Image: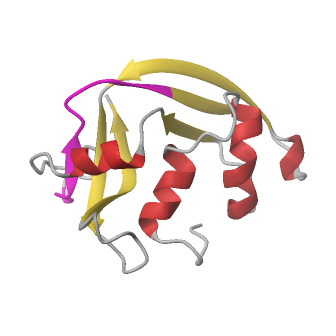
Amino acid sequence: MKPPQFTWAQWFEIQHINMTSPRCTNAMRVINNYQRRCKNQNTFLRTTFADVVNVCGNPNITCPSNKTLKNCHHSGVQVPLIHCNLTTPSQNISNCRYAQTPANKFYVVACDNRDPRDPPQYPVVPVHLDRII
């Protein structure tokens, strides 16, 4: 899944922060081309990477998706988000059609120590979107 030219944190940014267009069909092509498959579902948080890093400093909690992981952090505040839902698949990635559903919700993110390629300014960085509450 994860392309090797990217860190975990940079891949989190591709998939869940940086929407290259306000519409899901357009926005998703970036992710799908790297994945070499049309993802069935994907959430974009309308927030900045630095804001998610501040959330990574909130007190650690158990990851809702996996009760044995403990590197998760609740956002404390709500952010707008857009959820992309695959409505027509294709063997041609550029023909994959998406519908979208906006929302304003809390989120829970999983965070890890930074890779040398991330900027030194962030010792801990987001690596997985665990749960949209």
Please provide percent x and percent y for residue 117: 43, 77
Please provide percent x and percent y for residue 75: 24, 36
Residue at position x 58%, y 78% in the image? 4
Up the image or down, 49 lies above or below 11; here it is above
Tell me which colouring the rendered structure shows.
Answer: secondary structure
Up the image or down, 11 lies above or below 100; here it is below
Q: Quadrant of residue 79?
A: top left
Q: Quadrant of residue 118?
A: bottom left
Left or right of residue 103, residue 75 in this image: left
- Where are the magenta residues, as a range? 68-81
Outermost residue on the left side: it is 59
- The reply to whether the magenta stretch includes residue 80 is yes
Residue at position x 19%, y 31% in the image? 76
Please provide percent x and percent y for residue 30: 71, 52
Residue at position x 29%, y 54% in the image? 110
Q: Is residue 41 visible?
A: yes
Q: Quadrant of residue 106?
A: top left
Query: In the rendered picture of this protein, how many numbered marks are placed on residues?
Result: 0
Left or right of residue 30, residue 131 in this image: left
Q: Nearer the viewer, residue 121 or 76?
A: 121
- The reply to whether the magenta stretch includes residue 6 is no
